Amino acid sequence: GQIQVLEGLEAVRKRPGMYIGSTSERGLHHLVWEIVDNSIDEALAGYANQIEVVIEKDNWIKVTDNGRGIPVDIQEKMGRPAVEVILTSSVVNALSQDLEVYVHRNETIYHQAYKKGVPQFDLKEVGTTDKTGTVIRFKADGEIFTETTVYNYETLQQRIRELAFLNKGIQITLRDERDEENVREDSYHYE
Ligand SMILES: Cc1[nH]c(C(=O)Nc2nc3c(OCCN4CCOCC4)cc(C(=O)O)cc3s2)c(Cl)c1Cl
Ligand SMILES: [Ca+2]
Ligand SMILES: [Cl-]
């Protein structure tokens, strides 16, 4: 089961273009669409209505939603927490030099970190919460995206606006914190 995950990570990193269309600027932006798409599905299921995308210093991406939280219960299949099984089959995780999850669920904050899809430690309880949702922070792997790992605000802005227009009732916010002296935000909420 865990042998199958490792071969999956090797497959994705060996032929990344077969998975995300290209390793160009187009492929770098595709990472964000892959994560945001999961949060939109949680909203269409009726459980989330807010998504926030932050370009952080050094072109980290953080996506946050107010969904149920990715589940943390032990799979009978992997013997591992569900969230670990979901993220260690994620293309985004495989093509990120680092990725972090924080889950707010069961009044608990759970945390795991990964490098090229490989968990760095077991899922751990780190805090308490009265909210539910998921935070993902990732840094695209410079070894995969050799052309650029720099996001284009206007590219993200155009697609986030389109997603909010198509999926009415979802508040979707983009914020660029790369320059701490000049922070730019656009927030879309149709109907
Ligand atoms: C940023 C973000 N948010 C989510 C997210 O909230 N996903 C989420 N998935 C799930 C989920 O599915 C488990 C695994 N898969 C089912 C079949 O499609 C794909 C997911 C179950 C529950 C629940 O049973 O309470 C909650 C949740 S909340 C994911 Cl994944 C990412 Cl990445
Ligand atoms: Ca889905
Ligand atoms: Cl759970």
Image (tube, rainbow, N blue to C red):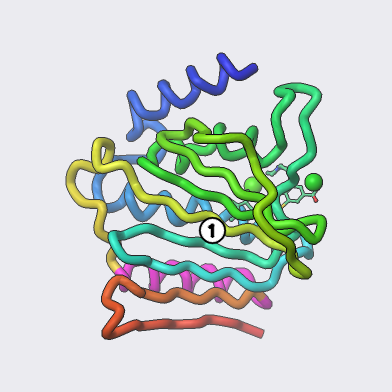
148 relative to 83, above or below: below
Where on the picture, by quarter, is residue 170?
Answer: bottom right
User: Is residue 167 rendered magenta in the image?
Assistant: yes
User: The magenta stretch spans which residues?
Assistant: 153-169
Question: Residue 148 location, x and y as percent?
Answer: 21, 51
The percent coordinates of residue 186 (x first, y second) are 44, 82
Callout 1: SS: helix
> Is 74 on the left or on the right of 103, as rendered?
right
Please identify the quadrant where the N terminus is shown.
Answer: top right
> Which one is nearer the viewer's eye here, 179 or 158?
179
For the residue pair 76 and 170, the one nearer the viewer reads as 76
Residue 11 sits above or below residue 32 on the image: above
**Residue positioned most to the front:** 126
Q: Is residue 116 magenta?
A: no
Q: Amino acid at mark 1?
A: Val
Can you say whether 119 is above or below 148 in the image? above
Q: Is the shortest distance between ligand 1 and the CB of mark 1 under 8 Å?
A: yes
User: Residue at 53% of width from left, 38% of height from top?
Assistant: 90
Residue 22, given in percent of the width and then of the height, sits at 30, 40
Furthest residue toward left: 147
* 10 Å crowding of disc 1: few (<14), some (14-19), many (20+): many
Q: Which residue is mark 1?
A: 36
Instruction: Identify the residue shown where x is 48% and y is 39%.
Output: 114
Q: Main secondary structure of the magenta part?
A: helix
Instruction: Name the foreground residue: 139 vs 149.
Output: 139
**In x, y percent, where is residue 113?**
51, 43
Q: In the rendered view, would you say 4 is above or below 25?
A: above
Q: Quadrant of residue 178?
A: bottom left
Residue at position x 69%, y 59% in the image: 127
The residue sitting at 71% across, 37% down in the picture is 82
| Image quadrant containing the C terminus | bottom right
